[PDB]
Image (tube, coloured by chain):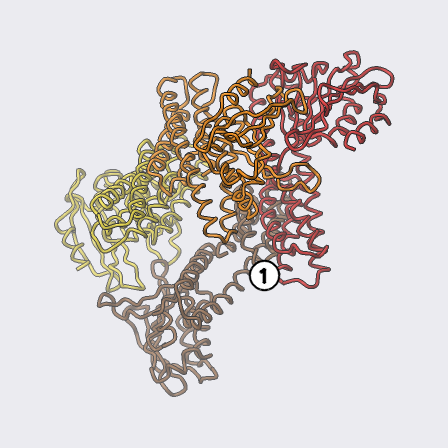
Chain colours: A brown, B red, C yellow, D orange
């Protein structure tokens, strides 16, 4: 049904201020589970989608958007039509490839060394939950069609944090190396919006951890005193940390750092067979991840 | 006037449940800034005080208590009379010498290898802020009554922290070396109380620091938002730390360490001419000091 | 040519004490980059290889070994024939799947909760650089033979260190949970050897780094004294670290941590166009990587 | 005899290029053990020495040089006559006071905030082993004769290191705060000479520790394997550290830092009743001190 969910939505059309995106023609791909979708913007040709429906478990599904009409390059890129399309894809695909040849902004940005995720195009995928990025710029006759941005949704909450933390490093490395105030300004603006989403995740991770610890030490009577102190202190540590994110304070990451340490200490020591200790150590570990990109 | 503050208090008398301590006779000692004070307990003779008023800068002031009445040895040592006296002396002298010949408990304890500060007699001085200790058992030739405990107040917070850390070392070493459970129990009880007083000082320094920040950001309207963020976050840092000290948690000093960092950062940045900033930066620094002995 | 490197080696045969492995028949699999290889042991049937040559960038290459001859199950599993084969495959595939149905030892071990990497079968893959493991016991619907071990080589040194750290966690957790001393002994023996190989890599990376610095400061005459101090001190840092690894000391990684810092500092500062500086900075960075898994 | 050693040497005279220092008149001081010595330079009056021979244990001996003839101020200060005099005093007194009123250089330097020890005058005392400094500049009618530099020889090897480490801090604090290149240059030149003496002390402390550890693990057979590894590794750690001081490398303090940690770990764990473990832990602790000012 995965295919028809696609075929049906594309046949129906995707509306936008820049025009409606409709399916032009479809064709069977290289393999049995591969298909090619040609799209139009209004009446004019837009781009092609190369899709893979997947074959569990060795083959992950993915989508490749390419063959963008150069006449529409200044219209499509950075438009709602662009957003609406990705909005659609993100609902079906965890892995995505985009040809950025016709995107002068992104190409220029990538050439000047911006991280793939903080590029104009990459930013649009980031907003939709894609955390892992790879910039292919090297074909050199070794791999055909070598100008694409690869983006994937995180495997786990751990992976999501791993990626954002890494992205933090690439960002700071780029800033110190860049000499373009206009470029740097755009990148920082994009990055800031990212921070907001990250801090708000710590907030909720903190609370879902706080309530979990409270419920633990309250109802679970057959526990140590070292354990009533672990879950106790952790609950307040997350409380302090949550307090700093709420006001979005600059000293927040220092606190999350401490809180993460004893949230980890709490999870390792209080984890057990009970449902109470299952969600206790669990919600602790969900918070520890939240702090990593800080 | 330093001498007359003394003479006036002893002439008036110092009352206690075991009797009133009054001055019997005073006499000029070997040197000009040296005097001998004979004291009575009720009507019976108690001991003699050898005092040195000091002569800045080469001579630190000190007091020597000796000639303890052996018949009253079991009534005085460990009594409020003993406490009230030291309480009095600690207000005037940074350095003190005490003959422990007539103190059987202290004597036995010192013989069994207990740290001077953790002896029955030594503990009472420790309570009053004396941190540096020396046990004389050798009259070393030119010292009369070569069975005395020497105690000095710390030069600095570093010196105070230095001394307590060293005592921590002698304590653990003693615990492993002694084979008397009754002895070890008494000592441990004393040491625990030492931990308490430091924490109790942190608890209170913490509150008086919070109130300083609370009143500052509240009433001081003409300040930055960076200062509003400084005093704000600090107030909560000290809040979190206070909670851990209150429950006497093992993770308390870890919190105190962090809170101390941004309390100092707050003090340096928010200090000013105003009474609000005078006490804000002030009370912060009092807490920072309080945390040092951890 | 990637396929023919394979076909040529299997046609030639791979010899071992338990017999020679030769290609019986090859056949086109479900997809174009998919093939099935039937193998014999001496003259008797052994197993089938399902291989994927890969299709950059969306498809990682992988190999699936299955259809193990049950009559040879006790001769093959744990033999040089098994080792020689994996040794061969590890040169061509970063991702591998192995059916452990006919491997009673591995089967029993996996059932008793041992980490996949630390199973009899899994350990042999671990030896070859495979760090990421997944135990399939659920055929999960669209997977034939749903009793397989999946192993992947690390993406990066961070990923490698990440995986080993996680395995360290599963290991200690398993030790506390199992009640079979014979089982625990085997596992611990395996894990210790893992520690060994990492250290043995550090030992050798350390020497090849020392020689690089030794030859640099010696032969490279046109260099700074800061560079003479860089390569000089580094050579001795690695010397000290090597001594601790050699005696297999518990304080070895502490030394490796420091030496790694100024080996990187040396590499960054002494790297240049010359062959002496090309290998100097080079061999330094190889040691730095070697220390990461600690 | 302590007095006559003085009286005899002063009567004999102290020769210098700037003239001979001879005793003019002597007089009994404030107390029984106090004396005043008036000195001449050639035939012209020089200064007065106020000396205290000591009275163990409560009274430490000290010497105060004051009443310097202003006509000779540019001749005496910074002369060999000045050095020879102090050379003499340092042989008898652990505590010294010097009026710096007639020393324009030192006064100006102290006024501009240089540490007492790194002043022109203070430097001369530092060379002779005096480590603790206090600058009295505040009389304000509270203490008479309030313009003196106080210098003391260290109580222990621990104290010596404590002082130098503190001096390192005052030095760096002053440098960043000062805006006089001529002044800063002089201070650094003085400080550098200090570093040399400090590094050479680590060298010998390292070796006296190295040989001590070798002798320990070699002859002491009834020791743990954790103990053969402690004393073993420490011996090599000090070796590496010693290596860096010998060439006087910039990365030296980083190494001493590590070595000090496991020299302390070695002393605590290997210390015992035996003469071998007495000097082992001992020589370890002598080295740990050496690293502190680094």
Give coordinates of residue C114: x percent, y percent.
40, 40
Vertical placement of residue A67 versus B155, above or below: below
Q: In terms of depth relative to the viewer, which is nearer, D215 or C157? A: D215
Q: In terms of depth relative to the viewer, which is nearer, A178 or A284? A: A178
Residue C48 seen in this snapshot: no
Subunit bearing disc 1: A
Vertical placement of residue A30 versus B122, above or below: below
Vertical placement of residue A196 versus D127, above or below: below
Instruction: Please report the residue visible at 61 percent of the width from the left and 13 percent of the height from the top.
Output: B141
Figure quadrant of residue D232: top left
Figure quadrant of residue C218: top left
Badge 1 crowding class, 10 Å Cα cut-off, few under 14, some 14 to 19, many 20 or more, is some
Instruction: Please report the residue visible at 64 percent of the width from the left and 43 percent of the height from the top.
Output: B244
Q: In terms of depth relative to the viewer, which is nearer, A120 or D142? A: D142
Quarter placement of the C terminus of chain C: top left
Quarter placement of the N terminus of chain C: bottom left
Name the secondary structure under disc 1: loop
Vertical placement of residue A215 versus D223, above or below: below
Give coordinates of residue D182: x percent, y percent.
45, 50
Instruction: Please report the residue visible at 23 percent of the width from the left and 50 percent of the height from the top.
Output: C222
Give coordinates of residue B107: x percent, y percent.
67, 15
Q: Which residue in the structure is indicated by mark 1?
A: A248
Residue D263 seen in this snapshot: yes
Residue furthest to the front in view is D43
């Amino acid at each position: 049904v995965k295919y028809e969910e696609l075929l049906k939505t594309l046949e129906n059309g995707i509306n936008s201020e820049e025009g409606e995106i409709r399916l032009v023609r479809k064709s069977q791909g290289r393999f049995k589970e591969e298909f090619n979708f040609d799209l139009s913007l209004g009446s004019k040709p837009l781009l092609t989608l190369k899709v893979f429906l997947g074959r569990k478990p060795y083959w992950q599904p993915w989508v490749e958007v390419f063959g963008v009409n150069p006449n529409l390059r200044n219209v499509f890129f950075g438009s709602e039509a662009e957003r609406k399309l990705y909005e659609f894809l993100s609902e079906h695909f965890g892995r995505i490839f985009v040809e950025y040849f016709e995107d002068k902004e992104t190409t220029y940005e990538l050439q000047k060394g911006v991280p793939p995720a903080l590029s104009r195009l990459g930013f649009e995928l980031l907003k939709l939950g894609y955390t892992y990025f790879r910039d292919w710029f090297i074909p050199e006759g070794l791999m055909e069609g070598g100008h694409k941005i690869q983006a994937e949704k995180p495997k786990t909450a751990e992976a999501k944090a791993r990626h954002l933390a890494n992205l933090k490093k690439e960002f700071e490395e780029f800033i110190g190396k860049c000499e373009d105030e206009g470029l740097i300004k755009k990148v920082k603006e994009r990055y800031n919006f990212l921070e907001e989403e990250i801090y708000e995740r710590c907030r909720l991770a903190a609370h879902h951890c706080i309530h979990a610890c409270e419920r633990y030490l309250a109802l679970c009577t057959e526990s140590s005193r070292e354990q009533r102190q672990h879950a106790g202190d952790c609950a307040d540590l997350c409380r302090l940390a949550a307090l700093l994110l709420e006001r979005r304070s600059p000293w927040a990451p220092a606190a999350c750092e401490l809180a993460a340490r004893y949230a980890l200490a709490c999870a390792e020591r209080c984890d057990g067979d009970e449902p109470l200790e299952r969600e206790c150590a669990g919600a602790c570990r969900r918070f520890v991840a939240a702090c990593h990109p800080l």
